[PDB]
């Protein structure tokens, strides 16, 4: 990744919070987003640097760009693409009941394309969810289509606590509660979330953890065969993104 000096960035309005991060609008000597990691253990900063490294080595129409990393005292900052309309989950809840199925199918295909690209390079995202899908274009006007960018996955899944992994249910693959196969589950859970206008299935941390421990399966979408195949507890039985992209 590219090293960004603190003199090259300007921190503006708070946008929201991610896992161990605060996300702000900013300027780069370009409008950007600044993902400020909390003062953290070296294992967490390393998992954050691994994400910056992964996203700086890939290039895809539907993957958000990473400008680089800035170290500002105890704060690690990932300088990433400012995407015009922000997260898909927020937008879906605001537009609940007025998002057509054809619009949702375009998003699913664009997301499956980004994930097929990663799968072919044997790279894991590990945080596929509506919150990490950003809208560059809304596709509300006649003759237009939405355009998504899959955000960086933030602090790597391998560095998170059990409590943080439970907070990720239902996007978290069940085998991760105690491989590219995990993104097939994240993809399936994101299709449910999109189908339900940003209302993902599953509640308290104990109820979510009990759901996976008891091997219960997620609700069917209101995409039924595809979610049923992606959301299986057997990782090797999940279809490839080549097959998913064909089935879509
Ligand atoms: C207008 N643009 C954007 C808004 C936004 N808001 C946001 C909204 C919540 C609820 C949470 C977080 C972490 C950010 N995030 N974002 C990103 C990104 N998180 O990578 C990239 N561009 C944008």
Image: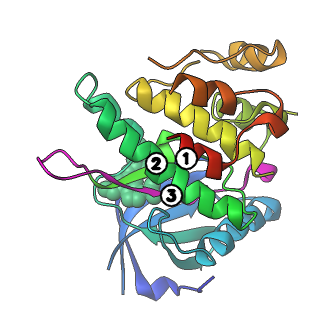
Q: Name the residue under label 2.
A: 109
Magenta segment range? 138-159
Which mark identifies residue 246? 1
Instruction: Name the N-terminal-most of marks 3 and 2.
Output: 2
User: Total marks drawn?
Assistant: 3
Q: In this view, does 28 lie above or below 225?
A: below
Q: Residue at position x 63%, y 52% from top? A: 242
Q: In this view, does 248 lie above or below 23?
A: above
Q: Do the residues labelled 1 and 2 touch (CB within 8 Å)?
A: no
Q: How far apart are marks 3 and 2 (CA)?
A: 16 Å
Quarter-of-image position of residue 7? bottom left
Q: In which quarter of the image is the N terminus?
A: bottom right
| Identity of the residue furthest to the right in this view | 178
Answer yes or no: disc 3 within 8 Å of ligand 1.
Answer: yes
Magenta stretch encompasses residue 126: no
- Residue 217: image location, x then y, percent: 70, 16
> Which residue is nearer to you in this view: 32 or 227?
227
| Identity of the residue furthest to the front in this view | 246
Instruction: Name the N-terminal-most of marks 3 and 1.
Output: 3
Q: What element carries label 3?
A: loop
Instruction: Look at discs 1 and 2 and give the one toward the viewer.
Output: 1
Q: Is residue 204 above or below residue 225?
A: above
Q: How far apart are marks 3 and 1 (CA)?
A: 24 Å
Which mark identifies residue 151? 3
Q: In this view, does 174 lie to the left or right of 28?
A: right
């Amino acid at each position: 990744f590219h090293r960004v000096d603190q003199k090259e960035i300007t921190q503006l309005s708070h946008l929201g919070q991610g896992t161990r991060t605060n996300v702000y609008e900013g300027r780069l000597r370009l409008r950007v987003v600044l993902k400020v990691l909390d003062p953290s253990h070296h294992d967490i900063a390393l998992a954050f640097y691994e994400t910056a490294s992964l996203m700086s080595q890939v290039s895809h129409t539907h993957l958000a760009f990473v400008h680089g990393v800035c170290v500002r005292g105890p704060e690690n900052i990932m300088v990433t693409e400012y995407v015009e309309h922000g997260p898909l989950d927020v937008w879906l809840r605001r537009e609940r009941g007025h998002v057509p199925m054809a619009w949702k199918m375009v998003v699913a295909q664009q997301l499956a394309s980004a994930l097929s690209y990663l799968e072919n390079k044997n790279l894991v995202h590990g945080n596929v969810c509506g919150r990490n899908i950003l809208l560059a274009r809304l596709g509300l006007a006649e003759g237009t289509s939405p355009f998504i960018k899959l955000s960086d996955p933030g602090v790597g899944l391998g560095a998170l606590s059990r409590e943080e992994r439970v907070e990720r249910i239902p996007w978290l693959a069940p085998e991760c509660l105690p491989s590219t196969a995990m993104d097939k589950w994240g993809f399936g859970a994101t299709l449910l979330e999109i189908c339900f206008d940003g209302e993902a299935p599953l509640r308290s941390p104990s109820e979510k953890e009990h759901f996976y421990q008891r091997q219960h399966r997620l609700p069917e979408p209101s995409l039924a065969t595809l979610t049923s195949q992606c959301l299986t507890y057997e990782p090797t039985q999940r279809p490839s993104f080549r097959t998913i992209l064909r089935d879509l």
